[PDB]
Amino acid sequence: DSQIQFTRHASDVLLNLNRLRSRDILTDVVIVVSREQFRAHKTVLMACSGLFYSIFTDQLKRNLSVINLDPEINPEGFNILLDFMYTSRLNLREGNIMAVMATAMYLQMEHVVDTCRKFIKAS
Amino acid sequence: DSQIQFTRHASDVLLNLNRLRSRDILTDVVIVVSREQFRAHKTVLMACSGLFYSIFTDQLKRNLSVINLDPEINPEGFNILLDFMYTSRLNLREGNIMAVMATAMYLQMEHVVDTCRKFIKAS
Ligand SMILES: Cn1cc(C#CCn2cnc3c(c(/C=C/C(N)=O)cn3CC(=O)Nc3ccncc3Cl)c2=O)cn1
Ligand SMILES: Cn1cc(C#CCn2cnc3c(c(/C=C/C(N)=O)cn3CC(=O)Nc3ccncc3Cl)c2=O)cn1
Image (cartoon, rainbow over all chains, first blue to last red):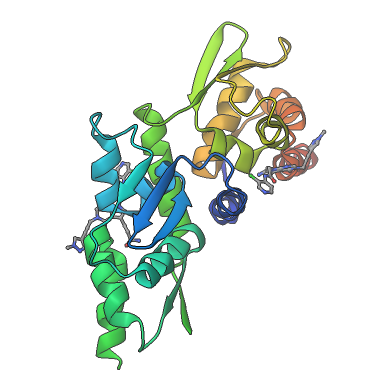
C-alpha cells in the first residue's frame, strides 16, 4: 500500500551486527589466517565476499565451522577487510594498499578492488 | 590511516541477507505466529527488535530454534515488520496501521512505533 523508506535502517542493522560480533554472539565460523584467527557470522561474510558466498552456499561446506585461508594471505589485510564488511569503512593507506588489494581480489570483493585501483591512480 | 566511506555498502549487505532469507540459507529460527510460520536469521532479528534481542542474548534461550509469539499478534502485521527488517521499507496503510503499530510495540521497535504515530497524525 503506502511504502515508507527508513534511510538509516541498513546502517543501524550493520552496526548492531558488528556489536554482536564484538561480543561473539551467534558467530558461527572462525577464519584462520596464518597465526591469527577471526570470528564472524557466515551470513555477513557471504553478503560481502564472493569467496565466502561460494564456500557457504555449497551444501558440502555450509556447515564448516573453521575456514583456513591461503597461507599467503596477510592477516592485517584480512582484518582490514573484515572490519570493512561490518562497518562500511575501509582503512586504506600507502603502507597497506597492496596487501588490501590482493586480499580483496582473493575474497572476490570487486568494489573494494576498484577502490584500491582508484587509490593507486590518485597516488 | 586513510578512511574511506562506502555509502551503499550497508544497503547492499541487507539486500544480500534478504536474498539468503528468501533461499532459507543459514536461517536458524522459525517464528510461529498463530497458524503461520516465518523463517529468519536470529542476528537480523536481534539487530532490529528489542524483544528478539532480549530473547536471544539470554544464554538460556539463545539456542532455541522455534519462538512462539503471543497468540494475539496479527500474522500480517508481523510479516510487514519482518519484511521491513530485511528491506528498510515499511508498508503502512490505513487498513494495517493499527495492527502494525501494536506489533511494533510488542517487538520493541521504537522508531517504527514513532513512524506509526506520525502516520496517525497525518491521517
Ligand atoms: C579476482 N577478483 C574477483 C572479484 C570479484 C567479484 C564479484 N563479487 C562476487 N560476490 C560478491 C561481491 C560482493 C561485494 C564486495 C565489495 N563491497 O566489494 C559481495 N559478494 C557476495 C554476494 O554477492 N552475495 C550474495 C549474492 C546473492 N545472493 C546472496 C548473497 Cl549473500 C563481489 O564483488 C574481485 N577480484
Ligand atoms: C512498548 N515498546 C517498546 C519499544 C522499544 C524499544 C527500544 N528498542 C530496543 N531494542 C531495539 C530497538 C531496535 C530498533 C527497531 C526500529 N527500526 O524501530 C532494534 N533493537 C535491537 C537492538 O538494539 N539490538 C542490539 C543492541 C546492541 N547490541 C546489539 C544489538 Cl543486536 C528498539 O527500538 C517500542 N514500543
